[PDB]
Image (cartoon, rainbow, N blue to C red; front, side, top):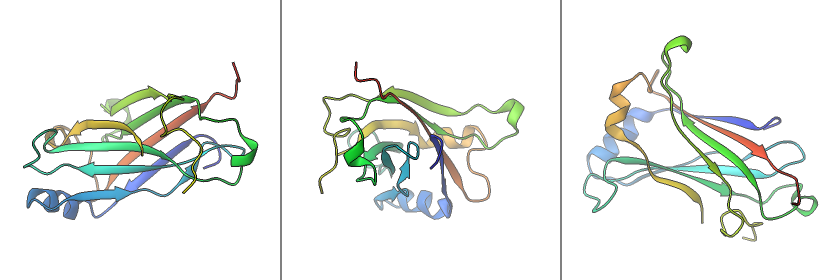
Length: 155
């Protein structure tokens, strides 16, 4: 990305929901994107927990990852900032009831450390059932929005 917000489109979503319905593990890897030209490179991982999972069953999981970037040697580490993850309600703009969370990066976590070769997010980001409570899936596609605010202050 150029600015600081990315929109990850996940199509063929219908087949994923049926896979998780018949007890088949599902994980999706998004493309890596930048928090800004001179910035950090991140990617997302989405999970659809099995119905037989002891904990967090039928929940959608979403984690953020740090990748190796072209400007790595030029930026301060670890990464600091505010990340907003949102599963977009595709209903009309004036009546959208999006589903999201906001988190501040934590330096002590190896998830925000400079890569060399573990992610951070929510195990229970959104229950699958919640998908039928709105028009989150339109045209067999789900939309995940990641908006990052980078803090370059060394304080």
